[PDB]
Amino acid sequence: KAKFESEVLTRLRNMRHKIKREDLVSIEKIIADREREWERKWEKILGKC
Amino acid sequence: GNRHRYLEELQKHLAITKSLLEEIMPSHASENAESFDTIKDLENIV
């Protein structure tokens, strides 16, 4: 029982680490690029922020 | 009194002790005694 529950804990940690270090880093980079591309595009068209 | 006499009286009572311990002790007493640490580890993991 102790060994099995330990495995469950490790699975949860691996899942959280995968979400925080892999999945959210990739998504946040895409969001930041998109927000910058957008701000540049309209700043050029409007001559102001 | 005499130290030999003392050890003889003590032997009489330790013999009772030995008989009581042989009666009280289950066959798996030693195994049960080893499980204590494992039980504590389970609680911490949860």
Image: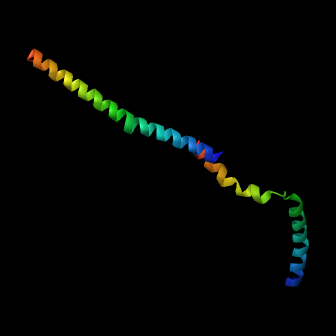
Is A23 drawn above or below residue B26 in the view shown?
above
Q: Tally the numbered discs.
A: 0
Q: Is residue B39 left or right of residue A8?
A: right
Quarter placement of the C terminus of chain A:
top left
Residue A43 pos. (x, y %): 12, 19
The residue lying toward the viewer, choosing from A37 and B30, is A37
Residue at (62, 47) in percent of width and height: A3
Residue B2 pos. (x, y %): 87, 84
Q: Is residue B34 left or right of residue A38?
A: right
Is A19 drawn above or below residue A44 in the view shown?
below
Q: Point out the residue furthest to the top here.
A: A46
Residue at (75, 55) in percent of width and height: B32
Is B37 drawn above or below residue A41 in the view shown?
below
Q: Is residue B11 visible?
A: yes
Quarter placement of the N terminus of chain A:
top right
Residue at (87, 74) in percent of width and height: B10
Colour convention: rainbow
The residue lying toward the viewer, choosing from B31 and B14, is B31
Residue A18 pos. (x, y %): 43, 38
Q: Point out the residue furthest to the left here.
A: A47
Q: Is residue B2 visible?
A: no
Residue B42 pos. (x, y %): 62, 46
Residue at (48, 41) in percent of width and height: A13
Among the 4 quarters of the image, the one containing residue B30: bottom right
